[PDB]
Every structure is written in C-alpha cells, then in structure tokens.
Amino acid sequence: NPFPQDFLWGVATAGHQVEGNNVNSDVWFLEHLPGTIFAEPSGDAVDHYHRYREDIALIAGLGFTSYRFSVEWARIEPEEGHFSVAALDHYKRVLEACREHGLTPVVTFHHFASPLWLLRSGGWEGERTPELFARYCGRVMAHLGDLIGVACTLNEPNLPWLLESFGIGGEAPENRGKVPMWAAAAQRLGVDASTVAPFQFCSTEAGFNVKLAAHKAATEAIKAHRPDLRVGWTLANSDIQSVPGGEEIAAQVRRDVNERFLEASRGDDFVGIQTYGRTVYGPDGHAPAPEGVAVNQMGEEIYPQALEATIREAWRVAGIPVMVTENGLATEDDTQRVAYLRTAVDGVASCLADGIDVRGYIAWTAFDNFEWIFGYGPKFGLIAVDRSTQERTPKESARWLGNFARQQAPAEAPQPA
Amino acid sequence: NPFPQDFLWGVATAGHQVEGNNVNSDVWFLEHLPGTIFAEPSGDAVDHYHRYREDIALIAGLGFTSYRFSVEWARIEPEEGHFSVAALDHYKRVLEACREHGLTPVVTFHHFASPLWLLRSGGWEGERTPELFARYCGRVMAHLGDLIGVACTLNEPNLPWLLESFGIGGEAPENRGKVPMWAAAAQRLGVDASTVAPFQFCSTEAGFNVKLAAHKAATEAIKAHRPDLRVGWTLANSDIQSVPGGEEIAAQVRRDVNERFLEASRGDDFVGIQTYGRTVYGPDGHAPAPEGVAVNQMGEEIYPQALEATIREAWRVAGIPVMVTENGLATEDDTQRVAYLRTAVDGVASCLADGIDVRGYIAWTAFDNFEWIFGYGPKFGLIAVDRSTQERTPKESARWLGNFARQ
C-alpha cells in the first residue's frame, strides 16, 4: 500500500463559496457593483455558516478523514482593529465539530475574500497588509489554535498570474480605472482605482512581495502559538504544456506562475498543490487545446493526469512534502467525476510509490457551490445541494472517494498498550 | 390579581443592542465614522445571535412568559431585493426556541437599525421606504409568521421628536451637512447629507409620513398572513409634566410627541407603551432633576409613577388596548431597580383595576447591552453579561420580576 496510515483524505470548501452572508467581504461588495463581472450574487450560498455540524457529520460518515475550510477574515476583523470574539467562537465550534467526528481540520486562513476595509489601504499591494494579516492570524490562533490540524496561510497567491496569461486580468495599476468594476469599486471606497487590488486579481510585483511577506509573517505568527503545527500556502499550479509556436510562452508561464512560487516555498513544512488539468500555449497564447476528452462542464479538457505532473514538479522545485489541497472536476455528470478521481488518486499513489512525500488528498469541492464569477452554474461538488431547501445529497463520487479513504485504514484487534 | 389569565410577563431586547456583528446595518456604519457621536462600537454586543437558546432557557427558567426581540432587516434583506432565507431560518429557530420554552414571542419587525443600503435611498424619508418595509415584513411572515405571538411593526417612531425638545437632534434637512457624523456618512455613501435619515434621528414631517405609511403598510402585509395576529407599534411616551412657566412648552411636547402618535394609532389592535420617567419643562425648557432623590445612572429622576400616567394617557387618546413593551431603569445598584419595578408594576395593576385593558408588561432589558450612542456604560439589564466571557448573571430584579410573573 503506497498511502501511509496518516495520509489525509478530505474534501475542501472556501468560506465565501459555501457559508452564506459573507456581507463584509470584498467579493460580496464586488458582486453587487454596477459594472460587475460576477454573473450572480453569492447570497446564502449553501448556508454552511449555520449547517456545518450536519455537513461535518455527513462528510465524516462518508469515510473522509479530513476537512479543509477557510476562516473568514471579513468576519473575524469586521473593521480594522475590532476583532470579533463571537465570530472566532463560531469557528471554534466548527473545529470542535471536526474533532468530535474524527476529522483533521485543514484550515485556510485566507481564501481570496478579504474584509472590505482592506481594499482602502491598497488591498493585496498595501504595505500594512503583511502585518495586519499576521496580526489576524495570531488572533485566530490565540482563540482556537490548539484545535487546528494543518494550516494553509494563503490560497493560490499565483492564480492571477495564470489568469493574466489568458488573460482576464493584470491590467497595469495605472490602467485599472478603465475596467468598469474597478472604477466603481474605487469610487465607493473613496480611493483611486489604481489602488484597488483584491487578492485574486493582483499580479503585480508589489502583490508578489505583499503576498510573500504575508505568508512569511503569518507562518511566524502561527509558529509562535504552535511550533509543532505544519504550515504552508497553496498554489494554483497547472500542468503547463505547449504546441509549436507556444514553447517560449509556456516556459515564461511555467516560470512566473509555478516555479517562482515553488522556489518561494522552500522554507515551508509543506506546499499545497491545487491542479485540475493542463494548460496549453500556442503562438497566440492560451489554446483550449485539441479536443478529446472533455467536455468538462466549462468546455475545458478533462485531464486528471495533470495532478501527477504538478506533484512531481513541486517535489523537484521546492523539495518539501506536498499536500493536494484541491483537485476535482466541473461536470454535471458525476460518472465523469468518478472516473476522474480514480485517475487522480492513481496519480497520487504513483508519486508516493516513487518516494515523493505526499501528505494528503483533498477533493474540490464538498458541496456544489458559488464558483466565483460564474456563480452557481459550475458544479464541482461531490455532494449535491438543492439550494432552495438546502438539502444535501451525496453523489456517487463522494461515496467512492470516501470509501476509498476508509479502505486504506489498518484492521487490527485491540492490543495491550 | 387584577392581572388577567393571559397577561404577558416579559423582558425585551433589540437585535442591534444584543446580537453582535450587525455589520450590514446603518448603525454599525455610523459607529465607525470619523466624526461619530457613538461613544463606542457595538462589536459583539452580548452575542445573542449565537447564544439565543441558552438566553431563552434562562429567561423562561426565571419565570417569564414572554420574550420581545427584533428581527433585523439588515440581515434579512442584505441588498435591496436580495432576501436571505438563511437569516430567516435563524430567526425561525429563535421563535422555535421561545415556543419550546413556553414563551410567547413578541417580535419587533424594526427596532431602529435598518440595512445600510436603505440610507442611500433617503432612509426614513425615502418615499419607497413604506413599500420596501412592507415587502420585508411579508417575507418574514412567509417564512415564520405562524410562530409569532404578537407583532410590533416599528419601535419608537416618535423618539427623535422627544429628543428634539431637549435640543438633541432635529436639524432641518438642509443643515444635516453641518453635523460631522452626517457629513462623513454622506461622503462615504456618495450622497448629499440633507438625504441621510436613519429612523431614530428623523423627526421631520416627511419622516412622520414615511413612518406612519410604513406602519400601516406593514400592518396590512402581516394581516395578509395572520389576520388573527395582534399588531401595533411602540411609542416613546414619557410622562410629560410642567412647573409654572413650562405649561405651553409641556403641552407642545405632549401634543407633537405623545398625542399625535397615539391618534395615529387609533386603528390598531394595541399600542405598545415605552416609558421610563417624567420629562419636566419649566420656563427655560427642559428641567434638570430636583433636589429630589435617587437619581438614575444618567442623572434623570427615578420616577416609576411615569408608567401609570402614560398608560392612562394612551387609553384616553388612542382608546385601544395597551401593552407595556418597555419599562425599566438604568442603574448600577439593582436594589434601586427592584423597587422601581415594584412600583411600576403596581402602577400597571392600578390601571387594570380601573378597567383599562392592559395586555402585558415587558421590562427593558433582558441583558446589560449596547445602549446606542452611550455604548456599554448604561446598565438597564435585569441580567448582567460580562462581555469579556459572555457569561450571563441574573440580577435580583430578574428573579423578582420572574417570580412575580410566576404568580
């Protein structure tokens, strides 16, 4: 068996995507702006904020051994310097639920959404962000740090560098004013549009430095409470490929998005790898590539072979233990998700059988949810939710993966201790 | 007793003062503005949002038969036209807890705090405000109306008029810009200050018409779900008195603040009376306490005889049943509170005994809480909360009044 007994089998969520009523967040604010690129508001999402106990019990019943979720800074520090012990107690009860159900909690301290007030100090390019984040992380540790299994500081700091290569984003700061969304944003924040920089859109050297310092200062804050607790960030590392004409563009992208962040990870306990497919570049940049085999729901290629390739890359470049903190598939046909997961798990086993220190596998996502700018259309969940009633119904993929996890545990009788 | 069989004995709260994290409300926003008049932010308050079950068990264990609390528009409709079913289920659970503990729930549909977005459309001077408020009251009824024991549409529409008589607000709208907090509110909302009108500061003719229209449209929305449910609004009615020199001033205030609103109440099923003390006017306007006892934490005269007066007044002007939806005392010494509640309650019984139809007594307030611009200084609670730990400790007044109910 290539998986060790302590290997984590989980599903992941992000607070804004499942909790509902993240009304103090930047993303919420962006969802309701006149010029918005968000297709619909998050609203209640799946109401994980109130239903987490039953959600945890469901997940643990399916045989998962871990649960990854975010603590939301927008709730914890709702205005700069005014921490909410009430919200911190909410997340302590979440962690207590995990622990009562045997789940190791993988806590993401930040998952794109920020308190809206942060966007007035320059957001993820502001020089105070690294220390405010770190202060924030110390406060969460102060209140519930003993209950965390594993810590992820930041989710996908490199995402917008990859989106820029499409590229959706990455206007120059001096040009953010010309996209409606940013112009509006700045106006109501009472601030200049060149200074508007939520986490997931910022691909600027300022933003690189701010992200890295925030990671660094947060790790230290966290270690001050639990020196034993393993910490890393997570990366949006695709399997980068090319066709003829795209070799140099592919190389540039692999370098700026993947290797640069993995180089920056080399001090850490682990790195989180988040991978869905390959990303192919030709002479005109991004090519949704040649066709076969997705047909994902978004019309992207179904290529869970990517995971094994990014795990290998991460081991090579960073040389630290890897945890797969996201992996999954957007599809309305769950039989495709099952076949995808079989292959991705094979990818993991294959890396482990080669001596790569992989420490868990966490599927994106637990429940069909708010897929950022595309809203509720894209279905990534291993568990269905009828949002109108909030009823949860596990899909076969949840039973398959859950039961795979369960079937890796030893089976010995009790032994005098 | 002269208390009928089904007289309600309650304690009351307001969602902004007790729940914590009312981050989408207009008040929250005003608490954090640069030139704010709020002495401190509400923050977590006493975290009633999370602890309500324990709070209601405690309330019920003490002997009360009723609980008055708000549902917060700021959480139910966080953006105009976007209702939260999860916020509605929360409140649904609050009502289920009440009933599980045998407590008749008295729900206030609005208790000063509004969604921040409402302030961008002219707030409680906004001409769409009545129909928005009614629509909101409808959604709440659709989700949970069957669990409400009594309904209070609006809390103290008339408060800011009373305060104006102390020269404490009531700038004409053209001069709102001159108050720092309004100028800051304006700038952050992208709106002119003349337009900024949160409920409890708005004592303008427009705000009278808007409040009244909202109360009426809300009443009609709630009866479309529950024609049996008793509906009214609550009034900030002091026992307005004079000394020689103050007669015209006193009559004026009595007419604009109490009688005008009681007249406006004449169609309703009951009027909620909220009274704490007397307000005395002399030749120089509002008079300070005499070399006359106690006094309360705010230096106002401790005057429980006020309640009997405002009940008699309401019966006379409105002519409909009276519910005491707030009465109590701000004080650090609870022995003063016990004595106050005893006499107030005697005042109520004396009204009852004269045939005035009083339907309930509800004390302000369950828990020491966020007293608006005064922050956590003032202690009105029958139950103490050490906010650092959120630990609840019933004062003697809790056990006194609870036990009084229990007979």
Image (spheres, coloured by chain):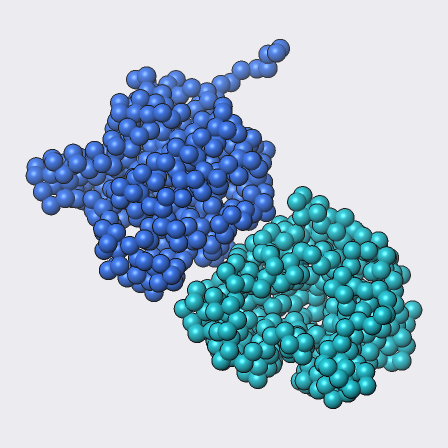
Chain colours: A blue, B cyan
Residue lying at 63% horizontally and 62% vertically, measured from the top left: B372
Residue A297's spot in the image, x, y percent?
29, 48
Give A290 or B32, whichever is nearer the viewer.
B32
Residue A31 visible: no
Q: Could you tell me which residue is drawn at 51 percent across and 18 percent down?
A: A411
Q: Residue at x 70, y 75 (%)?
A: B235
Quarter of the image with the N terminus of chain B in it: bottom right
Residue at position x 16%, y 34% in the image:
A251
Q: Nearer the viewer, residue B306 or A401?
A: B306
Q: Using the image, determine if residue A26 lies above or below residue A286.
A: below
Up the image or down, A206 lies above or below B35; here it is above
Which quadrant of the structure image shows residue A252?
top left
> Farthest residue in the left direction?
A245
**Image quarter of residue B8:** bottom right
Quadrant location of the C terminus of chain B in the rendered image: bottom right
**Residue furthest to the bottom:** B248
